[PDB]
């Protein structure tokens, strides 16, 4: 398709492929994966985190 | 005189020390009280046998 740039308003030189593609959301989310430790609880046998 | 020729260093140990008639039991922090401790049970089995 003939595509116009949304930043500059001038048209793009190459034609851009446009269509509906099925996209599925995966269970891996960054909110369930961000982690940080400053200092905290330690094991009883080896006194390391 | 013959202990150095066994390559034993006579200030680190003797032939007599190999066989043990005594045994040290480690401090409690080597083997903490909690699952349910079984290292203490292994020592208990040796005490029970004696």
Image (tube, rainbow, N blue to C red):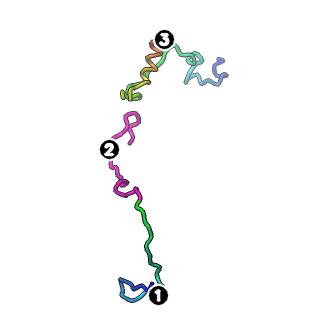
Above or below — where is B42 with respect to A44? Answer: above
Q: Let me know if residue A42 is in the magenta part.
A: yes
- Which range is magenta? A26-49
> Which circle's residue, 1 or 2, is located before the other in the chain?
1
Which residue lies under the disc numbered 3? Answer: B49
Q: Secondary structure at mark 1?
A: loop
Indicate which label's residue lies in the foreground, 1 or 2.
1
Q: Let me know if residue B20 is in the magenta part.
A: no
**Pointer 3: residues within 10 angstroms few (<14), some, or many (20+)?**
few
The quarter holding residue A43 reads: top left
Q: From mark 3 to mark 2, how far is it between C-alphas?
A: 43 Å
Q: Does the CB distance between marks 3 and 2 fall below 8 Å?
A: no
Of A29 and A45, the residue lying toward us: A29
* Relative horizontal placement of residue B13, taking residue B33 as reference (left or right): right
Indicate which label's residue lies in the foreground, 3 or 1.
1
Chain identity of mark 2: A
Residue in the picture at 60% in, 18% down: B15
Residue A40, numbered label: 2
Q: Does the CB distance between marks 3 and 1 fall below 8 Å?
A: no
Of A19 and B27, the residue lying toward us: A19
Which residue lies under the disc numbered 1? Answer: A13
Indicate which label's residue lies in the foreground, 3 or 2.
3
The quarter holding residue A10 reads: bottom left
């Amino acid at each position: 398709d003939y595509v116009t740039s949304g930043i500059t308003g001038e048209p793009l030189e190459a034609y851009i492929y446009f269509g509906p593609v099925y996209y599925q959301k995966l269970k891996h989310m960054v909110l369930d994966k961000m982690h940080a430790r400053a200092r905290g609880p330690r094991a009883v046998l080896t006194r390391q985190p | 005189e013959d202990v150095p020729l066994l390559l034993m260093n006579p200030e680190a140990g003797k032939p007599s020390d190999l066989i043990l008639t005594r045994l040290l039991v480690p401090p409690l922090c080597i083997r903490p009280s909690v699952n349910e401790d079984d290292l203490t049970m292994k020592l208990t089995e040796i005490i029970f046998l004696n």
